[PDB]
Image 1 (cartoon, rainbow over the protein chains, first blue to last red):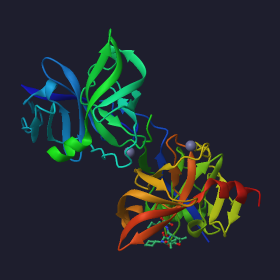
Image 2 (cartoon, protein in one colour; image 1 turned 180 degrees about the horizontal axis):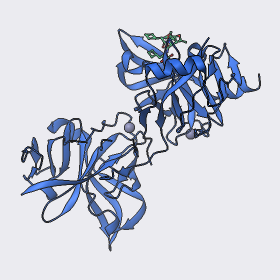
Image 3 (cartoon, chains in turn orange, blue, cyan, red; image 1 turned 90 degrees about the vertical axis):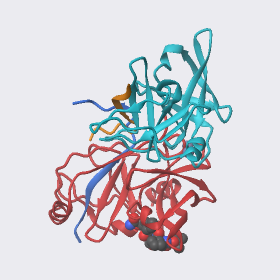
Image 4 (cartoon, rainbow over the protein chains, first blue to last red; image 1 turned 90 degrees about the horizontal axis):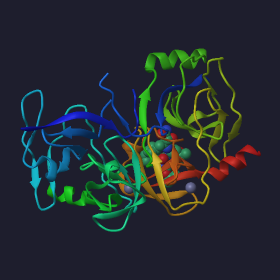
Length: 16
Length: 22
Length: 151
Length: 181
Ligand SMILES: *[C@@](=O)([C]([C][C]1[C][C][C]1)[N]C(=O)[C]1[C]2[C]([C]N1C(=O)[C]([N]C(=O)OC([C])([C])[C])[C]1[C][C][C][C][C]1)OC2([C])[C])C([N])=O
Ligand SMILES: [Zn+2]
Ligand SMILES: [Zn+2]
């Protein structure tokens, strides 16, 4: 099986 | 002379956020 | 936008990964020797280290790498899988006490997440919670120095 | 929570030039630090207590393009290298540093916060040196304390063979001083 990236987190809060 | 122009910004008030899919 | 922390999951569990210095690091106790998925197919780990509970593949798409701490502050902040920031006082190289104990479920799925210093720089990787009666009062982690040597 | 920052560019060369001449900028403003450019250089301007400050050697005595045309400087101190305009409508302002603090953090034009150790009232050593190029364009930027309060504004680089080891800054005190002048 594989590890799947289900989301991301931008620590600066950048919405751009 | 001319005027100083704002060409961008740097935001510090932002806090960790989970990037939206859309 | 690009994220430094990926929220990953295997068929059995969901945890976190933190891209630091080009590599997407996470905890061995969640991934093992599993490969990270990608559009081109699965990609193999660049590093694995059961002794350190550390493993890492090359940084995914839409990610950005964290910078290691260079100030050596002991006033850390933990980022959970929900993007909450938890201040943590550094008690030791791999140990830190929460500045406010939280229920055990508040730190779940956060293994692999980053432990940041006042400058938002990586100080370590959240290894596991040291709870008491179900309350996480302290945290265990893989200091970045280890990732720096492993890489 | 730790100090984190992100950058956004709001206009390019051609728009910048027009806006400089006309002095009429109608773009929305957000943030504490504004990336600023003249026809000769780009630097930064930090908003502290409702006032947008920057390094005199960058702003000179020019006006700031705003949605109502040019805006003359509120403060001008050639000797302390300071100039101030009313913080642009939309910006958020930092507040000066209470409790001094020895552990400083320089926010760069690229939105990077790099550790700096205070070695005096106006100088701090870079914990991890960087090439001068890295620091280019971030004059007027803020030097924060672990709490996120302005301690000073980046003014100079202590260069050694193309690598900055230390940085000279203008202490917030000089702002308060310049204001009563
Ligand atoms: C800032 O205005 C720049 C940012 C610098 C460029 C590398 C970081 N700051 C300056 O231009 C200041 C200005 C100039 C000269 N400056 C320097 O930082 C120079 N260093 C310097 O003068 O050092 C001492 C003597 C310690 C004060 C530096 C420039 C780059 C090459 C190496 C030398 O005059 C002052 C000091 C007022 C911007 N535009 O982003
Ligand atoms: Zn640090
Ligand atoms: Zn302070």
